[PDB]
Amino acid sequence: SLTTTEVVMENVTAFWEEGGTPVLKDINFKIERGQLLAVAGSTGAGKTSLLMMIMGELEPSEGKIKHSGRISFCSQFSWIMPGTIKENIIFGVSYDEYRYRSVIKACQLEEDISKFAEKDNIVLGEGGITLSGGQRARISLARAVYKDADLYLLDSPFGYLDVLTEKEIFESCVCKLMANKTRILVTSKMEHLKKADKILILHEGSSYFYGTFSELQNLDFSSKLM
Ligand SMILES: Nc1ncnc2c1ncn2[C@@H]1O[C@H](COP(=O)(O)OP(=O)(O)OP(=O)(O)O)[C@@H](O)[C@H]1O
Ligand SMILES: [Mg+2]
């Protein structure tokens, strides 16, 4: 009877356009501190909107959202500010060389940085147009992981990566480096769902499944979707 709960949603319904159809309807879940929740579902299902509710950017019309803590958010827009790679990753936080190194290794940036003589000190322009798609994605993830937060909201960080790079980062970063952090990972990959503490599958704004992977194996659409 000591509770470890970090995020709760109870009977949550929300509208982006207050009057039409809800973007999220009757959503219920809870995440305990240090757990990984995988959020899956087709394009447009409401996955990012769910993260937005957690961040206070979308308010419910019904229900309650409970969370107290610092959030770090890795958006679908893999964005880059003018400045160095190092400056992009640290992004206004205090510098901790041990932490910085652990994050660049876990996000598979070691080999990319170590390529130039100027290492991670070379200035990027806004957009980081001289980087590869995957470099931009990894720098964006590294930024979110470097922040010292209580809840990590990782919105499909692996979209632009090849399947081998994605596997290595999911294992080193999400599963290992962040093992004791509360994480919500938007992903529909079945291998990732296996490793999650809990799973929420959304469909057209409603909950299609919520529970453990063993509870999912016992039941489908998810096997088509993943
Ligand atoms: N800020 C917003 N204002 C108005 N409508 C929005 C907003 N954000 C999302 N929507 C709409 O709500 C629906 C759900 O969008 P959302 O971004 O949550 O989907 P998603 O599950 O993240 O999809 P994807 O996998 O494509 O990223 C979409 O039809 C989208 O057009
Ligand atoms: Mg999205």
Image (cartoon, rainbow, N blue to C red):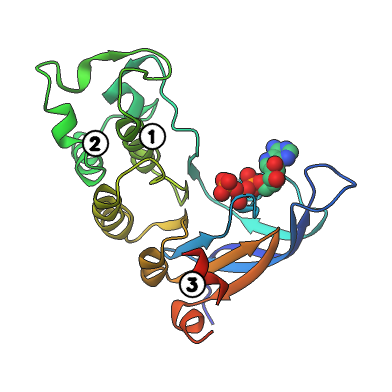
* Residue found at the far bottom of this picture: 218
Name the N-terminal-most of marks 2 and 3: 2
Image point (32%, 22%), residue name: 87
Disc 2 residue crowd, few under 14, some 14–19, many 20+, Cα 10 Å: some
Q: Which mark is residue 100?
A: 2
- Look at mark 3 in the image and give the residue it sits on: 223
Query: Label 3: few (<14), some or many (≥20) within 10 Å?
Result: few
Where is mark 1, residue-wise?
140
What quarter of the picture does the N terminus occupy? bottom right
> Label 2 to label 1, Cα distance in Å?
14 Å
Q: In the current view of this chain or complex, which residue is farthest to the left? A: 117
Asked which secondary structure carries label 1, the reply is helix
Horizontal and vertical percent for residue 8? Answer: 62, 64
Label 2 residue SS: helix
Q: Quadrant of residue 34?
A: bottom left
Could you say where residue 53 lies in the image, as x and y percent from the top left? 66, 49
Residue sticking out furthest to the front = 224
Q: Give the quadrant of residue 138.
A: top left
Residue 119 vs 45, above or below: the answer is above
Q: Position of residue 45 (x, y in %)?
A: 64, 55
